[PDB]
Image: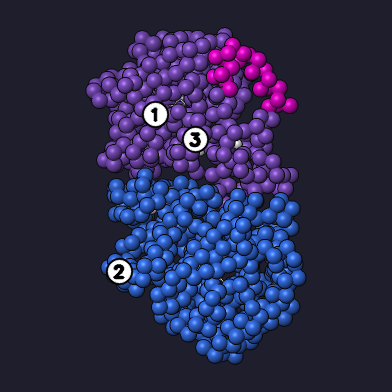
Chain colours: A blue, B purple
Amino acid sequence: DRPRFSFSIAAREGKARTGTIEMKRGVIRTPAFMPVGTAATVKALKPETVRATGADIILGNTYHLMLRPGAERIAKLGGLHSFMGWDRPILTDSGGYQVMSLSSLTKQSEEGVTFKSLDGSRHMLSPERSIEIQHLLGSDIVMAFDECTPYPATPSRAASSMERSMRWAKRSRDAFDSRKEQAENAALFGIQQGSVFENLRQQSADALAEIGFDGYAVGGLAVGEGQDEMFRVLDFSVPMLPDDKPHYLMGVGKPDDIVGAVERGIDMFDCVLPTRSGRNGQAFTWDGPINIRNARFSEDLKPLDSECHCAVCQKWSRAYIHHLIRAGEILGAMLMTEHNIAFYQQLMQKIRDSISEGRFSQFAQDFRARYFA
Amino acid sequence: DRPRFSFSIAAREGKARTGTIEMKRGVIRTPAFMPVGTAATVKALKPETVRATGADIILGNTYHLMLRPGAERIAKLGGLHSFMGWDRPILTDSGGYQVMSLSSLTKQSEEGVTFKSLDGSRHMLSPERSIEIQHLLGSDIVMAFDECTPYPATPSRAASSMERSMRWAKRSRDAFDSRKEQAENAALFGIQQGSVFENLRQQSADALAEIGFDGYAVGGLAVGEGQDEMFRVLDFSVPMLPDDKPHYLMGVGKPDDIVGAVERGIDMFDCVLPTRSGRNGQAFTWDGPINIRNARFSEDLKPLDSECHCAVCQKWSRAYIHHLIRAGEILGAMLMTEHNIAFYQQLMQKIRDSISEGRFSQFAQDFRARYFA
Ligand SMILES: CNc1nc2c(CC[C@H]3O[C@@H](OC)[C@H](O)[C@@H]3O)c3nc(N)[nH]c(=O)c3cc2[nH]1
Ligand SMILES: CNc1nc2c(CC[C@H]3O[C@@H](OC)[C@H](O)[C@@H]3O)c3nc(N)[nH]c(=O)c3cc2[nH]1
Ligand SMILES: [Cl-]
Ligand SMILES: [Cl-]
Ligand SMILES: [Zn+2]
Ligand SMILES: [Zn+2]
């Protein structure tokens, strides 16, 4: 039987790595893309379809599930896996991003964060409660409860925020370890903060490594800083993390962001872009994104992408999908989403294979030349 | 190879019949239920899923497709079957119901009907244009262009409407026959009108039989008359139609309506109820409909129906589907719709098998006793 957690690196090229994470519920091929399913569903897809696209793991969120249908309720019903019908690993975010994004709904203290408004209803999160919710969900990869520092941030505020997150990281560690069933069957990842500042990123990495985690996320990015800045921060931040554990870049991203992040040592990704923008009519192709709503696609018999191996591209035309999306038809959302998630997984497969073969640098160059032609 | 059209009756019980319609694109088992897909999609289902539920044929609509994406456009793209990815028979309604339902948008004459409002855009239908559109779509069963008489109607107005429909039926016949490819590969059904009046129903049946059609629809019902009245009209109306051709009751209906209509000699049905009410949270079960939104289902681990063989009932709980529908999630619509269409197809299968075995009367009684308990 598989271990609780084992990350193995099979091949490297520069800072890029490819390998596997073995967990009780399955193997995760890295670099990995995690489709997002905040409401216990990857929007518009059956779990079998998510799996058919090549996904090894999906992401859920403590915050959303706490509100609906409720953490205790999901536990009573047998856990998140049984509830939604996905039997493979699930990573759950801790709510720490919502601490920032929904801050106007919040009262924050060193103890935790209380969210208000069911109208005006209150829900509390803290390192202890976040870890408890993730246990109730039966999460396989549990994220520490942090605060995603807003961007931009002054060095003083970035430091204060990061320092609180490191204290919360220790509390997350202790809460996780104190629950035997969780400690024995799930993994716990810490989240590096520090905004765009090298010294704070170093302090955060050191604090997290001292505590010790199964994996290390780079938090606090993909919050409006832009690719140049994000890459600049990754350049110094990723090498600060333990080399022998997975590196997870939260919230990234567009295909080119993913490629560049892998070039900088990232092993795991999540983003709503393929799902959300899919429902909005944006389809990813090897020649760049297209908006299927555009009148130029109304009689285009080609598939969304000329090479894509997904079921959507095997069967339906751009013209049909154009019609569906224009008409607001549910099947439009379904087909766009399946194709985009499949595209993302094919991207990850090409990345993995090219690293394994020592030709990732060439792949990255070729990918960019064509995607941005 | 299969014929253009051959209806064979394999077994009978009272007025009920079971058999097959063989057409070039496939065999239709009767009594048959046709899922509705007005916008070139059965809402929230891939065609493969529609087929997996047991559907042999689906319904499209001349009116909706004329407006979006356009009949000529669909023809240019290779026809409706290729466009939407359903390779089996498709029946297309003629627009005659919309002549009534959208009458405030219309100017009507003996020549046809023009619909207004793309803002204020005009679109014309007539027997000739309706049949032409259905040809452009590549419909397998073409419906005559009629007018669904509003309900209630005075005998005078019902007569005038019916008489116009019979003139339009002859024009539909001639338009269909004048197009060699259509005449050789598709079938044409006439539509009986006459409101709730026996003498007008008889005149309409006689006119249609004199013209001659491949099948005969009972039109002008399921327009607010209620089951008692609908059944009363079917009691005298269905025997007026040629016995050796299919009898299609347009717009019906709830499960009990279908059972009673089969008891009265109906072979084919269409209705948006399982799809539309599915998206609205109504699930059909052998113990009657339930509304999955109801709080009583929030922690109910049972499938939607205890006996249903559909994929949804094999995998997901009422509690999960309750959550999805409450959350407005697309997967909620998908799962409810697949289950409801599967339920309807299982109903049709039970009807067919019971007629084949000479125990349909018993089935109808048992069905009603449990469904309305
Ligand atoms: C988009 N960029 C981005 N996403 C981020 C997320 C996930 C949001 C999570 O919240 C939901 O999206 C709003 C989804 O479930 C998503 O996985 C983050 N989560 C934590 N705990 N800490 C961060 O510093 C953080 C930074 C992010 N930057
Ligand atoms: C609901 N009851 C009912 N439906 C009916 C339809 C189909 C509407 C068609 O229009 C669309 O639904 C509005 C769907 O495509 C549907 O198949 C009818 N069509 C014709 N041509 N003539 C009728 O007398 C008629 C009567 C109906 N009664
Ligand atoms: Cl999404
Ligand atoms: Cl519908
Ligand atoms: Zn594709
Ligand atoms: Zn079912």
Viewer-side residue, B309 vs B373: B309
Chain assignment, label 3 = B
Judging by the rendered image, the residue that carries numbered circle 3 is B52
Q: Is mark 3 on a helix, strand or loop?
A: helix
- Disc 2 vs disc 3: Cβ atoms closer than 8 Å? no
Q: Which of marks 1 and 3 is nearer the N terminus?
A: 3
Residue neighbourhood size for the residue with mark 3, other residues' Cα within 10 Å, grouped as few (<14), some (14–19), many (≥20):
some
Q: Is residue B369 found inside the magenta-colored segment of the image?
A: yes
Based on the displayed image, in which of its 4 quarters is residue B366 positioned? top right
Q: Residue B113 location, x and y as percent?
A: 36, 31
Q: In which quadrant of the rendered image does the C terminus of chain A lie?
A: bottom left
Chain assignment, label 1 = B
Q: In which quadrant of the rendered image does the N terminus of chain A lie?
A: bottom right
Q: Is mark 2 on a helix, strand or loop?
A: helix
Q: Can residue B181 be seen in this view?
A: yes
Q: Is residue A156 above or below residue A250?
A: below
User: Which residue is depicted at the point 64% across and 61% down?
Assistant: A139
Q: Which amino acid does label 2 sit on?
A: Asp
* Closer to viewer: mark 1 or mark 3: 3
User: Which residue is depicted at the point 50% across and 80% down?
Assistant: A238
User: Which residue is depicted at the point 29% across and 66% down?
Assistant: A370
Secondary structure predominantly adopted by residues drawn in magenta: helix
Q: Residue B289 location, x and y as percent?
A: 66, 34
**Which residues fall within the magenta stretch?**
B350-373
Answer yes or no: disc 1 within 8 Å of ligand 2.
no
Mark 2 to mark 1 CA distance (whole Å): 46 Å
Based on the displayed image, in which of its 4 quarters is residue B93 positioned? top left
| Mark carried by residue B89 | 1
Residue neighbourhood size for the residue with mark 1, other residues' Cα within 10 Å, grouped as few (<14), some (14–19), many (≥20):
many
Q: Which amino acid does label 3 sit on?
A: Ala
